[PDB]
Amino acid sequence: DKISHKIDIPDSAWTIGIGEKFKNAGHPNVKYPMIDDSYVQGAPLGGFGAGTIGRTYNGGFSRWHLEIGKNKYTTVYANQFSVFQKVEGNKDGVAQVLYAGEPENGYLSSWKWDYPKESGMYYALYPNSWYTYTNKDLPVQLAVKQFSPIIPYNYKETSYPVAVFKWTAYNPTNKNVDVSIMFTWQNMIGFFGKQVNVNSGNFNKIIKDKSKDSEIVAAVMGNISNDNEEWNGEYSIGVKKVPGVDISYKAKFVTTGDGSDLWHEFSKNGILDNKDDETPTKQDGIGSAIAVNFKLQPGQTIEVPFALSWDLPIMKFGGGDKWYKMYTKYFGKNGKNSFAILKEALNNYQKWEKMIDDWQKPILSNKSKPDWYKTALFNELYYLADGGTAWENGKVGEKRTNNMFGLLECFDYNYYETLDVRFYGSFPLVMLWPDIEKQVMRQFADTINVQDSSEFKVGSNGAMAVKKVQGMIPHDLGSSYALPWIKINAYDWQNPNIWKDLNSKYVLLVYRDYVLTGKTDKEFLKYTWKSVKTALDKLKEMDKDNDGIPDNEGIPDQTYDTWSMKGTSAYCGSLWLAALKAAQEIGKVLKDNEAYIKYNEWYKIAQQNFEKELWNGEYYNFDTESDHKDSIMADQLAGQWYADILRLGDILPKDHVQKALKKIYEFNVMKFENGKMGAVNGMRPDGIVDESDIQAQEVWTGVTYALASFMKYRGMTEEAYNTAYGVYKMTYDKSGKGYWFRTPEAWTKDGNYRASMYMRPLSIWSMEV
Ligand SMILES: OC[C@@H]1[C@@H](O)[C@H](O)[C@@H](O)c2[nH]cc[n+]21
Ligand SMILES: [Ca+2]
């Protein structure tokens, strides 16, 4: 490996060998079908709301999130980079697809598949990833850096449906070597969203953009239809000329054939036919190829950038609504703009690299933090793009000031912005994209007094319940299978209108968003104030014994949606205390004296009774009325965790908080698989895991990272990082279960999981407050 020194990969990048088999992989531990796409994954490409494409560590374009809200795992085999090399003096060269695998059927059988093992590495530090190719039959060593311009405090480039592939080639040998790099792509119009005739009318064209000191050559893969529909648009691949390289291309090869129409050209001398051909296809799948060829002398390095764009302007949801995607603000809505997007990337990628370096540098340059922590901190952010992210720039046929946004809970539970989860998972948005975060919270504010009296069947018990109650915050803002932003509370396993955490978490999120953006946004507090007061006032009505605290009802009426709480719970009780303190402070800021007084009065009574009912001398009891009320809950003081972040001070005595945190580390962490797997949710005082429900026996990745944050703020530095390390290990390490780029909600002691690709573990960013 002589190529590593010619590029700059951070030591904290996650690494794996190209073609590596992983032996320890976890699988779902639930009874009904659940997504398991395997451990062959990678860091995604694509901006927020753009649709994303997961290119795996084996080189394949395999995890398709281009249909917004859906996860489709299938390798499109025509989509590849390939290499040709010939040493000066030899009669033949060699050609090789850079993919550690082969197609299942006979399509593209002429291509040279099965990139060999132990011949290259994959590296990832989101939004960047890299491959190196160090192969005994490839004298010239190659590397690529791939990325999309995902940039904090930037709402423009961050939305773009584009990826850059910056290649570096170096000749460590003593002979001249001719080298070609080829990018192939299938015309994927019709891959989704088209009910019949899926390739019909697809056609490819070549764009040559020549202007002084610039030549770009690109293929634009579109359809002859000018219809404005979810399925229609364009893909483009292309390359920018640099000194010492020539460009060749092939506009049309057949993907549903043996591929020799292309490969016979590339494998001979690494140079394509430059054949333009705009003939549309009928049944056959078609693709395009863009290549560069150059000669490298001994010791010579060259850099060449390729790019990929996709202009699919319209997203359609299952309930029928069609919306334009955010990037259309910058490039247009007609779906004929892929080249413009590609060109912007090829002409500005060096600037984008620097912008990414500039935001990663403060963390990467901090030598007090271990590299493993940096690996997790950056790579967990994959989910902001990969989470079915929807970001609208108008309803088709409809202009407003704001652009609505939604991140999925996950794909198995296809709900936008699940609020009990975003309480944990939204830290990166408030910290890095706060205008999105505040927009999402205003979306929730607007729903507070919505009332939908139609009824739905509650999954857990079969009872009928009202869809949406006035004054109750919704669980979620809908499903991609239905109508995001329009039809809320798609979730139906429990009735969220009686949940005891949503209204308090809503208030805490509002105040968090004010505090963590500088305590300056009075306008945001003003916008949300009526909803805050309404939310707390409605929750107070659920106090059934006048102890000043809402009563959990002996069912799962909060985020642990199969784990029953009854009476005053540590979890919901502490959230309530903190929400009351937050509302007091908002009242002060807004000069609402009567609100300050009322919430102060409720706070003092509730605080006294919380302490009386639950403090047992060592920790706070799970609740006051359950069968295992004395279980040690990992999340027992979630309200105090948020109070620390919001700078609301002590809601409970410092000494008792410290004892409780120490107890949690001693038990829920250290007595669970020797503290190497995170914090199990519920542990009995005898040090055996609580078996009352499956959720008690689960480690929740987002709960554990948030607990680590809590410990860290409280000066329990070793405990904090040790607790978080188990989550990192299970997700990324060779000794873990292979969950990189699909961090799940939960695992059990055997390491098997529930709900991969989950929002909650984005809470690792609470460790950076
Ligand atoms: O894992 C627990 C989570 C809950 O916290 C969410 O509120 C809910 O939408 C849901 N559905 C399935 C699983 N879950
Ligand atoms: Ca009560």
Image (cartoon, rainbow, N blue to C red):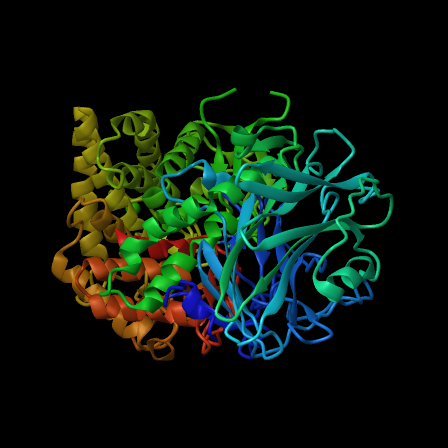
Please name whichever residue, 737 or 325, is drawn nearer the observer in this view of the structure: 325
At 28% from the left and 41% from the top, the residue drawn is 512
At 60% from the left and 37% from the top, the residue drawn is 210
Residue farthest toward the right in the current orientation of the protein:
282
Residue farthest toward the front in the current orientation of the protein:
89
Q: Is residue 159 above or below residue 735?
A: above
Q: Could you tell me residue 718's position as x and y percent?
A: 22, 70
Left or right: residue 692 compared with residue 658: right
Q: Quadrant of residue 108?
A: bottom right
Q: Is residue 511 above or below residue 288?
A: above
Left or right: residue 761 compared with residue 574: right
At 43% from the left and 42% from the top, the residue drawn is 498
Q: Could you tell me residue 610's position as x and y percent?
A: 22, 51
Please name whichever residue, 376 or 300, is drawn nearer the observer in this view of the structure: 300
At 84% from the left and 40% from the top, the residue drawn is 279
Left or right: residue 306 compared with residue 123: right
